[PDB]
Length: 36
Length: 36
Image 1 (cartoon, each protein chain N blue to C red):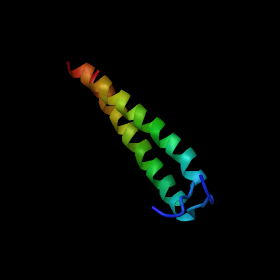
Image 2 (image 1 turned 30 degrees about the horizontal axis):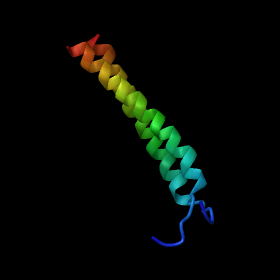
Image 3 (image 1 turned 60 degrees about the vertical axis):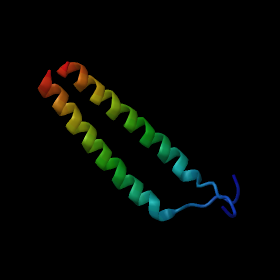
Image 4 (image 1 turned 135 degrees about the vertical axis):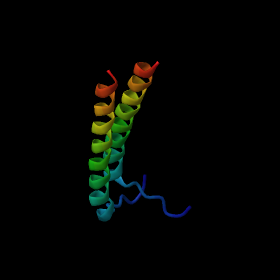
């Protein structure tokens, strides 16, 4: 679009959110293994 | 709104987040198939 901007704060926040999503995915896979 | 801005960094980050949400959804569907 126009006038690109780098929201430096969201980068750290997005890294943390990505880590928590990884951990949620790992827990879900553990549940799947348990059910199997 | 006003003065549109393209946060080029979030685009890559959003792609990664979308991939992880896809994988979470796939795991949830696998759990559902297991329970059924």
